[PDB]
Length: 257
Image 1 (tube, one colour):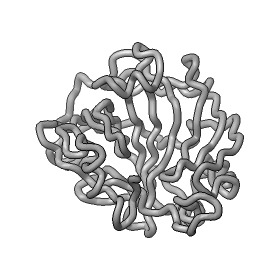
Image 2: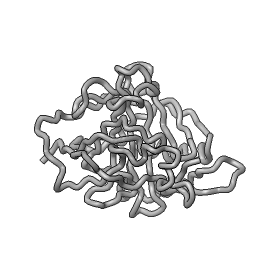
Image 3: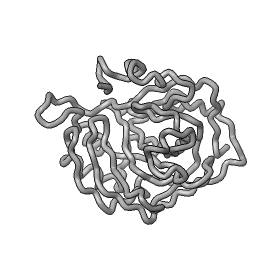
Image 4: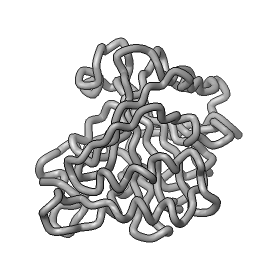
């Protein structure tokens, strides 16, 4: 099955998931000089005060921190969005080295990692229905650079030893995702896709201009995770990013000048 290795990586995905060569694939390179400022785009509303995290899971490609999405407890609204999008999970993509790891790029620059906060449009009732809709998901993407530690990440880093291998889960309650946000909510936005199979073209991407900083130690701990299950041959979970895809007939809009 699909992965990020020599024989099953992003260049192979199209064989099982032909939409990989579709018209609205993600990620993309964000050319800051060609993005259009759209003064009518509204400020994002991020309402995470009642968020209920439940669990953290190594799924063999990344780890997901999962939330109770059976009520409007953590929601994204405004910006380019119509309606209310509920937080279901977040996960990251990261590199084997600090010079790579992000999925989106900014003027071809790669960051060390990228955080994806995944939300689904409540008009569709559940996540599985939402992913079948062109406006089903809103993903808040946040770049990570290496520098000072991010204290709000540390609880995640701590628990990684409990979910080293594919299929392992751990209780992960009371995590506050507001500790993963930068100061500014200035963003770019464009229509795209999931960046892992099934690659569905259901995402309004909202990519923050300002990265967060994490420490070398924090990223190193991500790089100790394993793609494999316990008792299978060890392969470090690194470089679990899809490269930039053609923009095709899309314009990236900016909330800021």
